[PDB]
Image 1 (spheres, rainbow, N blue to C red):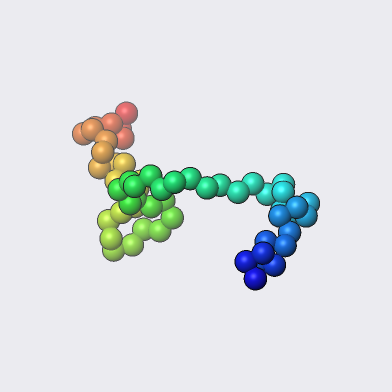
Image 2: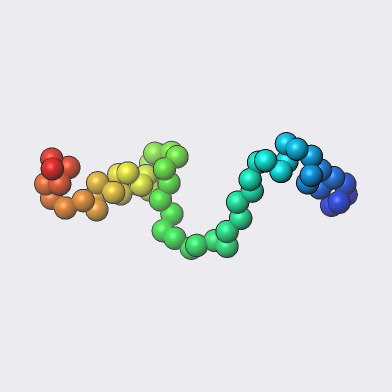
Length: 57
């Protein structure tokens, strides 16, 4: 069933869609997608990485 599940690598819908795989860069987990109680939202992290008085610039 591994190979009946990969029955269509070569239908036209499944070639034009590109597939990304990368070996995981182990990076500090900051997430664009959801801001919640864990302070990991990357934009909030980026404003914290801004120097004092640069968002006014």
